[PDB]
Image 1 (cartoon, rainbow over the protein chains, first blue to last red):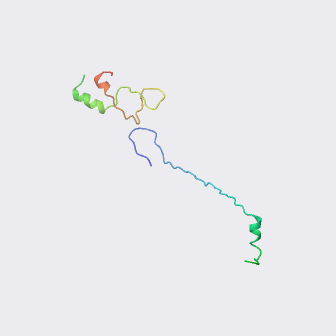
Image 2: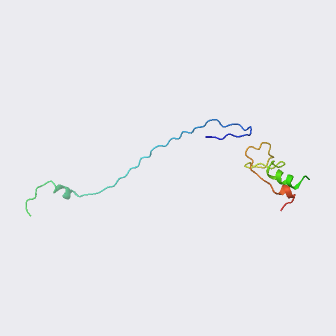
Image 3: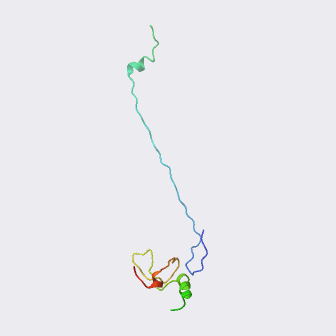
Amino acid sequence: PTIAHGDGRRPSKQRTFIVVKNCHKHHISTEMELSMLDLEILHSIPETP
Amino acid sequence: NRGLYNMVNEYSQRLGGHPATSNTEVQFVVIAGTDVFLEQPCSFLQEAF
């Protein structure tokens, strides 16, 4: 908005602002390790106790 | 030289004789008092601190 004034000052007309905001992307990673002997015996049915 | 009440009135009513500008690199004289919001108490008493 504006104000009316009594001086002869140059008058600011109607004004308006346009602003833009954008996104940012973030990434997360981690690494875990497992042995093959461990993964292999998940596949085979166990014979003895 | 006018009355004490004329001095009191002129103090706040009519802007002083050629005060400096603000928000400039150096001090130029004021010709157009758009937003001149100043008062000066040494003009009344003619003394410098």
